Every structure is written in C-alpha cells, then in structure tokens.
Length: 218
Length: 214
Image (cartoon, rainbow over all chains, first blue to last red; front, top):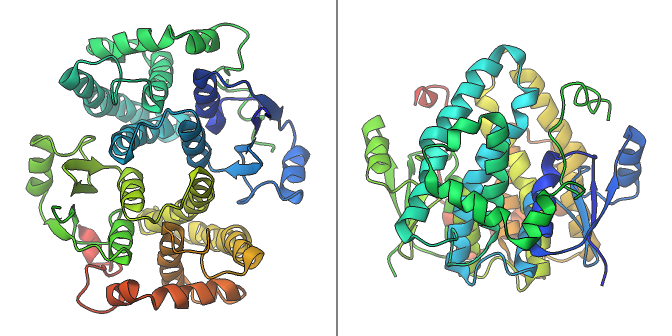
C-alpha cells in the first residue's frame, strides 16, 4: 500500500543510493527533509532512530536505519538481490567494493584540507588500478549485459550510480574501460533509471562547499 | 563440501568475525595465514582477490572477498540470518550498528597518537549512550534469550563478540546493562561458542604493541 518514506537531509549523502534503487525498481516514494537540528532531535526523541541516526526509511511498518539494512530489504522485496544465496554472494562482494570506494568519495569533502591532495590521488589510483579493472574483468569474463545472473540487479544500479560520481570527479578515469562505458549507457536507458536521471526527479545534486559547512550546524 | 578456507594474517583484524560465525555454526574450517608481503602478492597476482585485499574465504567454489559478503553468505548457508525478509531487516539493522562500533574499535590503535585519547573517549560515549542502550532496549522489549525470532542468529554472535572487545577496552562499560551481560553468558555457554572460547581454537588474541610492527 504505502509509499516508502525517506528521512534525510535534502542532499545526496547516505540516502542517495536508496533513492537510486527505489527509483530503478519503479517504486514511488516520499521524502521528509530534516532542515534543522530540531527536526533531527524530534526524530530522536520520538524514538524513530535506533542508533540516533539517519538515513531512516519507513517501509512496510518498520523504521529501518542503517543504509545497508534499508538497501538489503529493498533489493530483496523487488527481486534485485539475485535468485539465490550464491548470486547474492557475488552481488554482495561486488557492491561492497563499490561501497568502499563510494565511501572514500563521500568523505573526501570532509577530508582534512592538508591531506585532500594526497587522498584524491589515491582514490583516482584505486579507481584506475583496483575498482574499474575488477568490474571490467567481470563483464569481460561472461560477456553479458549485467553484472550477475544475466539480469538487472542492485549491483548494476549501485555501480552505475558510482560511475556518475566518478565522472563528476574526473571524466577521464572511465576512458580505458569500454565495458563500464557500455554498462553505463545501457543501465541509463532503462525506462525507470532514464526517468530518474532526467531533470525534476528526486535525484540530488552534488553538495557544494558553501552548503556543507552550513549542514554542519545540525 | 570443501572445508571453508580463510586467507588472512595470523591475527584478529577483519577476519575474526567470520571465525566467530563459522565456529558458532559448528562448521570446521581451515586457515592459510599470510606471513609476508610475497604471500599477499601471490594471492593478488593469481587473481584470487577481487579488490586486491583479504579477507578472502574459499567456500562452495567461490573466492569470496569483502567481510560483509563473506558474513552474509555464511549466515544464510547455516540458518543464522533469520526466517524471512523482515527478520533479515532487523538483523541487518542490528549488525550494521555492531559493525559501525566494531569498526571504530578495530581502527583505534591506528589513530595518530595525539588523537588517540579523544577517539577512545568518543567510543566510550557512543557505547554508553548509543549502542548499549539500543541493544539493551531490544532485549527488554521481548525478554527472550536471542535478539531476533527467539532463536540464535548472527546478531547474537556478532554482538557477543563485540561485548568481548568492549570488555577488553573498559570492563565497566557494560555494568549498567544487565540484559547484555546475561546475553554474553548464555551465548558464551552454547557448546560451539564455548569450544571456540577455549584454548586451541582458531580464535585469535588481541594485538600487542610489538605485534603491530606487522
């Protein structure tokens, strides 16, 4: 019946991969933006947040916190977690790599300014030499359109999301990886994702530098 | 039916929670310790580490890397991931909390020394104010012996592992949490876990100052 309700800042942050996944699955959701310290305190004092944190998603009568919990639940419900325990293993392995990399990119903006130069270079080296090669190799090994089981799964969605963030960081990093490029294009033209990528969707922009040091106040 | 094979340093690190999970499920496994930079290099070069890192576990024909992938697979295989999607959600929410706190503790002795006292104080605050209250609350909510579905799940095992690390860090942290102290004892007395906690198991010691020149 009910639309998932997403409690987060009006920003990408740790809720954006859920927006991508729900949108990819064709699921219409509502959002309730935390705009002040008091909004967050009200979620806390109302007992909505198990560990005092957002993201939180109201879905099927649960108040799910922890990004991975929310995502695991959504992906099973909408058949984007593979067909069995072994396909789930490949998906989890792949998406956890994506998450480790995504986490490095997510936190880069709060990086101590004196180590931003070093770290950015490292993230680029890891993208070039560790992550992109690993996914290019998987796609080459089986020659199929999707990462796992020859059908759309959360892994394709989480990877493609990440390809957009890497493109924002440095458009050249994907250039020597043709199969990642083709995957990006295919996934981006699935009706649901195409709609999500179009102006007007719930997809969120990059956090700007002026509007992050303002989201510290909460 | 190969025995699962765990490739990791001869240390706790990021493989310990898998050692606890397998042992708790009564699953006999083997370990191949990385002792040199060359051991790691050979695994990387021979294509067995998808992201050039361990932990890696050989199980059911896969070379599984990423802790969470390894743990999720083992939990499902041995019926410690609950009965349906909604129990998995509760379990996931609990264990992700456990892993966030776990991660902080894991990385503490690698903090630059002039931050190390501040990090510890923040960990203890989170333990007393965030994490222990959350898990005490769940235990009192249903008053049962297990976190979820009135039967042993990975959540019990991951939590009780963490209560052992929290004990090592500060023995007083658990003192105002009687349901947590009771879970530690009960889980620790399950035959499999009891064996694991006894000498001669694959359970690993804390790192010592001198061992960290690894």
